[PDB]
Image (cartoon, coloured by chain):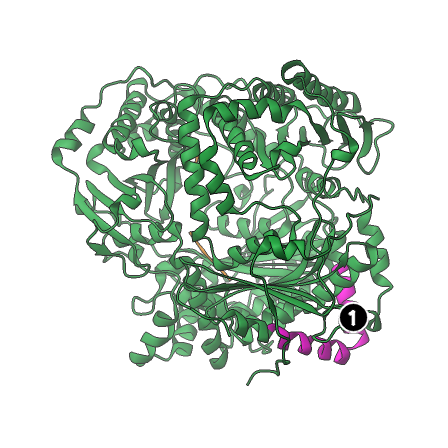
Chain colours: A green, B orange
Amino acid sequence: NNPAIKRIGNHITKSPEDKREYRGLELANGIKVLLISDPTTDKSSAALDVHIGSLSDPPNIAGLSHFLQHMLFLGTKKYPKENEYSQFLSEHAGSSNAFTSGEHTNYYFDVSHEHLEGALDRFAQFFLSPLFDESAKDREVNAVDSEHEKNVMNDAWRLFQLEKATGNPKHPFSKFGTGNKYTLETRPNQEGIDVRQELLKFHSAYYSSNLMAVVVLGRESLDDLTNLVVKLFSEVENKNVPLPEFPEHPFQEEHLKQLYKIVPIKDIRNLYVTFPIPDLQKYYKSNPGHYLGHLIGHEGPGSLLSELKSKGWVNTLVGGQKEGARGFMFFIINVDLTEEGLLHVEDIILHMFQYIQKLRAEGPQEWVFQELKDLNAVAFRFKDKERPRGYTSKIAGILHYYPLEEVLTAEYLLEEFRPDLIEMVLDKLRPENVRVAIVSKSFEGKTDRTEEWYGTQYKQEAIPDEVIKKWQNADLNGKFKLPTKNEFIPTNFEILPLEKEATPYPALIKDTAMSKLWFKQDDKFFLPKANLNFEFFSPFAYVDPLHSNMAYLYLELLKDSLNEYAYAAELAGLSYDLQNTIYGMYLSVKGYNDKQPILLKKIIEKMATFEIDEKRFEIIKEAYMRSLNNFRAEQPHQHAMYYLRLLMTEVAWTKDELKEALDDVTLPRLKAFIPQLLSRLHIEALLHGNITKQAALGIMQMVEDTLIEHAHTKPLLPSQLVRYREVQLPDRGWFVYQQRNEVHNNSGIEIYYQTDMQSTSENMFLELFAQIISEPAFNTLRTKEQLGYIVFSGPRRANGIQGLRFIIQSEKPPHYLESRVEAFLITMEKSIEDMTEEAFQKHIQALAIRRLDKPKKLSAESAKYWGEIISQQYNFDRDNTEVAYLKTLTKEDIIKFYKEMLAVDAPRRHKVSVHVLAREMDSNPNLSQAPALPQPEVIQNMTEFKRGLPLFPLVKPH
Amino acid sequence: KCLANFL
């Protein structure tokens, strides 16, 4: 008997482990709604997803819905201030974002739990009466231009758009979703378009209530959340819009049997193989695409990848189904390519078809379905609790595809075995349907076409009928086998009882020469899961460039050889991370703590007795070179950060030094290095989860024992445990290092104001100041001044030292950028004077909320501890300490700080700037006032610069 | 074993 609600769903199916509460419903205007009650939650969240996206852009205005998406954040009739929304979130511990896919536009935020309504009210207005202010439109068009600019030289985006340009040009699929200055301003002006109209018109046409899903998560009751959503959302007009469909596959007859040869930006070798398939979405309960994805994409013994890897043709493979839109989908198999592989594409593909053929011969396999189903059931039951923001965003999307009651389970639980569908999809994976793309630098200058939006150089060709024929007569090949029963599937899920001496924080339960063990039994999440983290120290992992190279290579070769065996563990929710650090090695094992000791033992055993394959060494090494080389293609702002890291750390080997040194790495040299590296270690570890003190000690000891037994590993001296220091900058000094990015026609800049070592007080000064300037910086440098898409500020922490930093990627030159940040900084101090006492306390409260946000899942908690451990601060209770301290602070305290350490004529200003110039810039010489700046000392040489300066102490361990 | 524009 409520007119506003069309219906309430029945029980929404949750995992029995899920303590949160749920209600599905549909509003009278047709909006689908999921409500989530979590009385424990620190942040609340909501999301709205409109079932419209760039596929419904007017053909004459590419990127209009992406543009529209940017614009809704910039003011509504009810809250006209350009950044009310942004600011409200900022000063209530929230944040927000949005994205536009071809069929969706998805808007979400989080906020402190007790300001849901405030946030949500402002949020709702996006869908009721956006202003699309005229001067906002003029400015924001640059943000989008910048967004696209950043993607132009990116290889993923180029391939993404190239696929679209090589299908039916008539099809909506072939549209350019991002837009830029040209398509959103320049061209529309020439063509007499009033864009504020087109934005108003499009919003009015498509932002209909019938195409909308809303998820809201908060502490309130389901009844309270119900009234709330009804109140704010039933006034969204139902313009009854038919939901767009795309029955016609964008790849028609003439688009099949085609071969594309593509020149990349980075030096990569890839083979993309694509088949068009119908929309499988409706079969979600049986899911034939997943079954075939699992199989064709398998990596274990007998798998397709396995044979291609053995022939030295490929290193990695992806396969399975790929979204298109309502009405069409793709089935893909993409591999990377060794130098041999490039010359055997025809053979690669024949093996692809031989494997597929094997799947035909053997037919559909219920036990494989059974396994997939059980894994998913286990995954679902024991799923980690999500951060609310991502959770709401995601459910909002799927509300458009699944009955209310199933929204939680529909992407997990499989129900129906369908050999018919498996058969039917399989029948499409045939040589007469194939599209083939080869990406390689060897097509330089051998190409005759250009994709218009990105400038992608490529050539197109009919695959010869004779070749199709060869692929069509693909024999069974004896090296291909279905995978066998997965022995890694966990079966024991008991939660060990909480020991009498479990502690709130990790305890140091072992402190010896060889190893230092931190342990905590999970007292929070109760899932049959564990995290085992190991930091291995050796001075030989980074003693020089050559040694870095070897530490890396060793670890890549190990992973590569372990791959077949570990893949099974991964499907079973048991995975591992293994990489070289500037201190030695890092190992993390994560997942169900049933079969974990097994995988761990296999790993240590392998590293300690490693036997290197000659051919695998050559391939991996070659890849690593290209990898180091390809750095030159990273974004200008990534470059900026890279250089700052190199400038400020005591020891740091450059990519140039690494690639230069990489020629000296021979098979002999590596074999000698491993036992050398392994012969003396210290291990510091975090064991955290569903395990007991006994189990932990045994796990740690088993690791140690395996190393002794096989590598004769003995301890390291306490004095050898060398942590690197941060370079210490001189009062009133200012240095600039400048370099050029040769791929990107944007510039990047990082500005670092070093303050002092970390410590309760210095941390909180920096953190509070960052909180206050956080939103205004974004708002000034981007929204108002439109300096770029990437605009960032906040604390920088490294080697126990800290400071404030700004990162901007922009079309304007770095000296210009410097100027405007400096201007901004004056604004901020002026603003901190003008701001009320409350405004100030609000900011304290926001920081507090952020810092005190409880981890929602095991990994998140481990991460916090691991931060304390690797930084050797071991300040496990730091959050209450630092928040306790924060509340003490006043306007005076922060003004003092800014005056002392940050202001342009600060007594203790310590400033480094990294300038990364655009491809085309050559030299490096109404809006608020920018102060006159000192003569910068231009850093000529990094070694010299470092030798000429003090180094900071290392932080005293808590 | 298995795109979109951010704000």
Give the x, y percent position of residue A748.
Answer: 51, 63
When asked about the image quadrant of residue A843, the answer is bottom right
Q: Residue at x 84, y 73 (%)?
A: A892
**Magenta residues, start to end:** A821-848
The image shows residue A193, relative to residue A585, as above or below, that is below
Instruction: Specify whether A108 is left or right of A519.
Output: left
When asked about the image quadrant of residue A696, the answer is top right
Q: Residue at x 66, y 31 (%)?
A: A538
Asked if residue A833 lies in the magenta stretch, the reply is yes
The quadrant of the picture occupied by the C terminus of chain A is top right
Count up the numbered dots: 1
The residue labelled by disc 1 is: A900
* Residue closer to the observer: A122 or A54: A54
Name the chain letter of the residue that bears numbered label 1. Answer: A
Instruction: Specify whether A736 is left or right of A105.
Output: right
Q: Secondary structure of the magenta portion, mostly?
A: helix
Give the x, y percent position of residue A397.
Answer: 49, 51
When asked about the image quadrant of residue A80, the answer is bottom right
Q: Residue at x 50, y 65 (%)?
A: A789
